[PDB]
Amino acid sequence: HMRKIFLACPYSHADAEVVEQRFRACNEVAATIVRAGHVVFSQVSMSHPINLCLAELDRAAIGRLWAPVDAFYMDHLEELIVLDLPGWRDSAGIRREMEFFEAGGQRVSLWSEVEHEFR
């Protein structure tokens, strides 16, 4: 029972420190999922370090560049876990991902609700 998890997390924020904190929080949860032996695509873990190299583009432009890339991962993974940090209900990536997985009949969970399944 090796799970294939798309791990979503709120990202964009006016305050760069908040973005960094969300990044570090997502990295820790992704680490927990990996330690438990599952496949994860931690969207923020891979994109944040890359986004730092796209400083010339603005928040909105970045979101669009990632859209078809995130879709590749959505398409090949089996369930969605949303790391429900403050601001998660206002995240663009998150609403989209929840809708995609939900409509497809796939499992969607909040980390606060399933953290116990990984320890």
Image (tube, grey):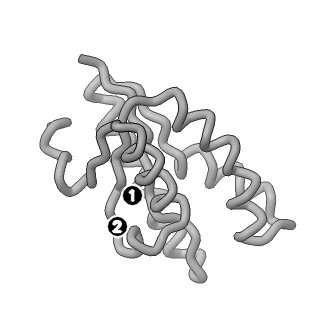
Q: Which residue is drawn at 83% across and 66% down?
A: 57
Residue 104 percent location from the top left of the image? 41, 38
**Is there CB contact under 8 Å for labels 2 and 1?**
yes
Asked if residue 89 is positioned above or below residue 114 in the image, the reply reads: below
In the image, which disc is placed on residue 112? none
Q: How far apart are marks 2 and 1 (CA)?
A: 9 Å
Of residues 44 and 80, which is closer to you in this image? 80
* Residue 52 position in % (x across, y down): 72, 58
Q: Mark 1 points at which residue?
A: 25
Residue 91 x, y percent position in the rendering? 49, 68
Label 2: which secondary element = loop
Amino acid tagged 2: Leu
**Marker count (numbered):** 2
- The residue at 54%/32% (across/down) is 75
Relative to 5, is 100 on the left or the right?
A: right
Position of residue 84 relative to residue 78, above or below, is below
- In the rendered image, the residue lying farthest to the right is 56
Instruction: Residue under label 2, please give it.
Output: 85
Instruction: Give the residue furthest to the top.
Output: 1
Of the 4 image quadrants, the one containing the C terminus is: top left
